[PDB]
Image: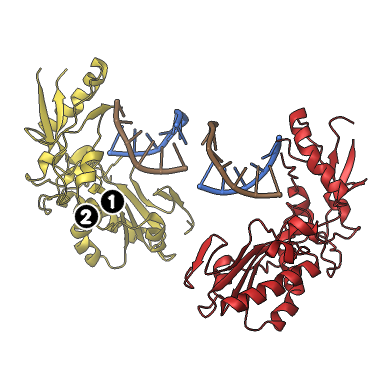
Chain colours: A yellow, B red, C brown, D blue
Amino acid sequence: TWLSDFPQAWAETGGMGLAVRQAPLIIPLKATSTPVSIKQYPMSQEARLGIKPHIQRLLDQGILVPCQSPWNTPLLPVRPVQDLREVNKRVEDIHPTVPNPYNLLSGLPPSHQWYTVLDLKDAFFCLRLHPTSQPLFAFEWRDPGISGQLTWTRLPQGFKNSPTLFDEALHRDLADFRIQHPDLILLQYVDDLLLAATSELDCQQGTRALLQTLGNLGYRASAKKAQICQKQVKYLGYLLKEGQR
Amino acid sequence: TWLSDFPQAWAETGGMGLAVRQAPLIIPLKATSTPVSIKQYPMSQEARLGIKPHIQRLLDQGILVPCQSPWNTPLLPVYRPVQDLREVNKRVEDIHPTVPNPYNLLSGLPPSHQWYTVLDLKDAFFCLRLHPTSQPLFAFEWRDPEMSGQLTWTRLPQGFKNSPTLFDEALHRDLADFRIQHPDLILLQYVDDLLLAATSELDCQQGTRALLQTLGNLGYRASAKKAQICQKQVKYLGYLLKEGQR
DNA sequence: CTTATATTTATAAG
DNA sequence: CTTATATTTATAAG
């Protein structure tokens, strides 16, 4: 199967990801910015107990570490969601290089109608965060047993530049693959990937190369939602069918 | 004084005006327009008594007359009577707006002419007759507060969207000859607001005398109370004219 | 949790 | 008089 031939490429079998080729990211602040520290709002014991295993897994994986930071933003109960809006306001903007899905799909020619669709799991966490920038994203945590600050050692969710920074990182890591397979079409939308070939055979071995490449580089795709070598797929809210849409 | 010298030309001495040279105006309607009759709102006795003397004066002057018309628009209940003619305005064909804005108007005022006379015409619209065929358009309902029927206007009425333009056009036609017979004077017209500018004080004196005579003879009436005659400094259209400035 | 985003009178007019 | 112009949350999000 596709699962057994490529255990490092699937999130279910390959372990949490780490883009080994990508240096830890530095997050430049606006010249005006000084740290913002927002008090954590209280939460029910149920919410805290629901958050706990997620925090604990991230701690065990080293994705969260203890810190002491002049920054602090609230965690909210919804699994954990961090309100980083006041950090986002203080981070310098970067040029938006991610194409909108419409333009991205315009690069899909009729000649390639065999599709594989993959979504990368915990994509942002594959990218490391430079220690100088880790204090920006600190929050307060108490196990449901004393309170302390934690922050992220990887690119975090809710950070405004995470999608663009990830898209640019993966483009660098898949550049060679594109060279080694000039007859394949590869669409990247952050963590959503579409591979297209003219034939099922080319799609089969092209998907083999892509999965091997992704796992080697330290990315992990969802085997659950993978659509592999199919004439009909869903991608970015579109149904791709008979060369349409 | 000017008051006695030109009694026909002043509102205070010459009575209500009438532009005798202007044919009664016909008011064309839009191609689909049908008469509109909207009910008169009630009004307090206080308001009715306040309006009454104004209505009676206009009846006595022939400016209002009884009528029966399929058109009817309201007199405002709250003491000068104000007629809401908006529903009539919607049904009257538009005309090209020929009145210049004051700024462009004043652009024709050169610095050579720094002797000014300003006149404003009293009850200007009422000087232009309204042709009987168009009078039914402007009917409203009146009941005397002590002793009910429709009245309408035999003159161009207030609140009619084309009254300023139609008056400005009529007066431009009527003062065209004055303009030719007095090439050294500058004459600015803004509906019922007139500025006469001259090179010397005596030209302004003689020119103003001729303008008043011409206005009176034509059937228009200027306000003696507010007139600014032969001055180096006048108020005109919100501006203070002075040294040839503004 | 917080927050960026999408009915109500004051005039003026006729 | 009526008409035209100039404070409030529902929600989606972090």
In depth, the one of A111 and A86 nearer the eye is A86
Q: Report which residue position mark 1 lands on.
A: A190
Query: In the rendered structure, which disc, 1 or 2, sits on the residue that comes first in sequence?
Result: 2
Same chain shared by disc 1 and disc 2: yes
Identify which residue is drawn at 74% across, 55% down: B12
| Residue placed furthest toward the top | A45
Label 1–label 2 contact, CB within 8 A: yes
Disc 1/disc 2 C-alpha distance (Å): 8 Å
| Whether residue B44 is visible | no
Q: Secondary structure at mark 2?
A: helix
In depth, the one of C12 and A28 nearer the eye is C12
Q: Vertically, is A208 above or below A41? A: below
Residue A90, by quadrant, is top left
Residue B162, by quadrant, is bottom right
Quadrant in the picture for the N terminus of chain A: top left
Identify which residue is drawn at 23% across, 41% down: A122
Identify which residue is drawn at 37% across, 59% down: A104
B62 with respect to B232 (left or right): right
Q: Secondary structure at mark 1?
A: loop
Q: Report which residue position mark 2 lands on.
A: A170
B33 with respect to A71 (left or right): right
A16 with respect to B226 (left or right): left
